[PDB]
Image (spheres, coloured by chain):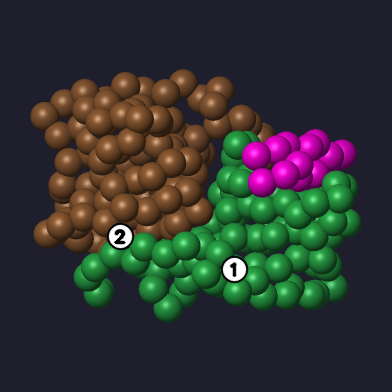
Chain colours: A green, B brown
Amino acid sequence: GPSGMILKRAYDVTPQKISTDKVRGVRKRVLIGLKDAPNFVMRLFTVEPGGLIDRASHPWEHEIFVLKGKLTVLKEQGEETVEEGFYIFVEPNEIHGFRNDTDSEVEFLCLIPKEGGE
Amino acid sequence: SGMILKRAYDVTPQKISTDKVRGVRKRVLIGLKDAPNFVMRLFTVEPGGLIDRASHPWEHEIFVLKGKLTVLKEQGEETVEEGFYIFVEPNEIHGFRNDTDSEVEFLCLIPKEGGE
Ligand SMILES: [Cu+2]
Ligand SMILES: [Cu+2]
């Protein structure tokens, strides 16, 4: 493929609104997307206060790193909150979701294999 | 289980000190034991630390978490700060240095073919 390196301020990517049956109060920046990625993509999610990524599962994993705030993680059984500096691994097909129960924006990096989209 | 939630700091850093890498610690957050496709590491570069120029047949996806990171390119260099992401194409010459007086941290993901 192509050569070179991209170095860019993540906030120079505009946050795009995500609105689906199971997602509300969320915006996403695609940092390293399908157009460039050999294998996996990098997104930066912003969860607004009260925003919800409701429980779901899908045939690919997540690798997540929490950048800002207190994130509530929804599990098959119950929930647990983590904060900036936590990582999360979600195996393929594992039930998961996220909620922001705080009054300030939560941000996390979320990487998936590119077969799962961007 | 099917979900791991952990404070990255709690993962034991590994000291690296070789002919090409000095003053660097590496945490493997999501490693080969868990990862179906790609691995997640967190590097700490001490003041004056160096990851010297190299290339390899896999990409890097990096996010700068803390500090001012000097990025070595095939020729020359570029400094970036916390809040920058870096995509290094496969085979591109790259490395890293910390010219500041405090620790620099960055997240670094590679496909599993690259090891952890
Ligand atoms: Cu998901
Ligand atoms: Cu490298």
Label 2 sits on a secondary structure element that is strand
Is the residue at mark 2 in contact range of ligand 2, meaning its CB lies under 8 Å from it? yes
- Residue B108 location, x and y as percent? 40, 46
Give the residue pinned by disc 1. A29
Q: In the rendered structure, does residue A79 fall within the stretch colored magenta? A: yes
The answer, for residue B107, to whether it is visible in the render is no
- Marks 1/2: CA–CA distance: 19 Å
Indicate which disc residue B88 carries. Answer: 2
For the magenta stretch, what is the residue range? A68-84
B110 relative to A81 in the view: left or right: left
Q: Are labels 1 and 2 on one chain? A: no
Residue toward you, B108 or A107: A107
- Residue B21 location, x and y as percent? 20, 32
Q: Does the magenta stretch mainly form a helix, a strand or a loop?
A: strand
Indicate which disc residue B6 carries. Answer: none
Label 2 chain ID: B
**Dot 2 amino acid type:** Val
A71 relative to A115 in the view: left or right: right
